[PDB]
Every structure is written in structure tokens, then in C-alpha cells.
Amino acid sequence: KVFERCELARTLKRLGMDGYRGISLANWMCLAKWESGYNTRATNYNAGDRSVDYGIFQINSRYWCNDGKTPGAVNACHLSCSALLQDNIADAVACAKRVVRDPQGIRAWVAWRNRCQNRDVRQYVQGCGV
Amino acid sequence: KVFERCELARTLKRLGMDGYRGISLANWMCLAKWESGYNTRATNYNAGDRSVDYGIFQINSRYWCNDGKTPGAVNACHLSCSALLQDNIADAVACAKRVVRDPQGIRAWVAWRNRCQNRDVRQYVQGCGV
Image (cartoon, rainbow over all chains, first blue to last red):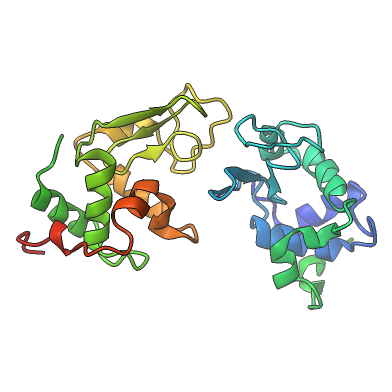
């Protein structure tokens, strides 16, 4: 599912994401926009280590979710990766909340560092009632 | 269908493979050569991950196509692996173009690295009129 900007914003707000671990709703949204274009069904293949990135927040099968086909796979989120390709993003948010608990934080996502960090991210939440 | 050298060279050319992603027709031809011997029906089973490589470009069933018997399958090319075994290589071409959109490009194939990379590949297209 491709959420519409404001629809994703209110949902992530409702799911307790604004100010989670000091991360604003506008940053979560900026991450989602650059990772997947707000599409829950997005994926990417990492040929170097045989992992795949799943969902709206592009969570990797090597450390976070289990897809049963990634060597050295840890399942810190304790959920199948398929669960992160669903229209209902509750599981993805809970896994994203786990990711940023690591001593790396939201900087775990490279694209966030390159497209959101230190930049104006107000557009992501402009006029959504959040 | 096992294509003859120049027949495939000309087909790949009309399907817009020359120069695609910086990859010359000659490199694509060298890939076809060492991956499948130019055979659209070639398949390679890997006992390790239990996945199968299909057709002329030997596209793997883990992330690219769906063969219905590979758990955790992500079907990034949006097609059954069987469509990659047909005489018409249009879908195989479309799927190959997708694979090389990744950063490493054609270097994703082990055989290309072993047999084509850093080598004079002009042999595969000479005499073909392309």
C-alpha cells in the first residue's frame, strides 16, 4: 500500500512515533519517503550479504526480521519479514521502534543521514493535523 | 531455444540492451554465453539455498521471479520463473534490466566476473552486423 502523505503522518502519530527516542514525526516521514516512497510492499536486494530490505521503513532480514533465506540472520524484532509487507504497519512500527533502540539510532538508515539529517523536514508533515 | 550467437546479439540490440546501464551488447553476450550457453531452457539448482537460476541470463528464484516452490520468495520482476524459460526473451530481458539497476550492475553474476570482466569481449559480437 502506498499511503498518502498526510494519512501516513496521522497513523504514525497515532502509533506513538512522534518524539519516540527523541525522533520527530517529520523525521520518521522523511525516512519513509526516501526508503520506500511510503510503499509497504517495497523491497531491495543486498547481494553482498544476501539480505533483503522490507517495507515502508526498509527493515533488513539480516538483523531485524526472519525471511528464512538470509545467512547469519538475527531476528531481534522477532517477526517474519512478510509481516512488514502488509498494509497494516503496526508490526513495522514496532520493529522500527526496536531498530532505533540500538546504539546507532535512526542513523541506522543511511538514506536518512543523506536526505534528512540537518535538513528542513517540515514539508513531510505540513497540513496534516498532527 | 538455443540461439545462435548473432541472432541473440541482434535480439538483445532490438530490445535496447546495448549501452543499458553502461553495459555494452558484447558484455551481455558474454554473460549469456557463460551462464546458459545461449539456451532459454537452462536451469541451475543450488542445493545450498535450494533456489533455482532460470534461462538465458540465469536469474535466481530467491528475489527475482516466483516459481511457487521457494519459501520467502520476493518476486521483484513480477513474473513466474517459467516465463523466463520461453523462446521469446522479452520478459527475461525486462527482468535482466531490473537486476542491473542495482549498484554493482552486471557484476552481480559470478560467471561474468570469472569469464568476462577485464577481458577482451569483442569476440562475442564480431561478424554479427550490430
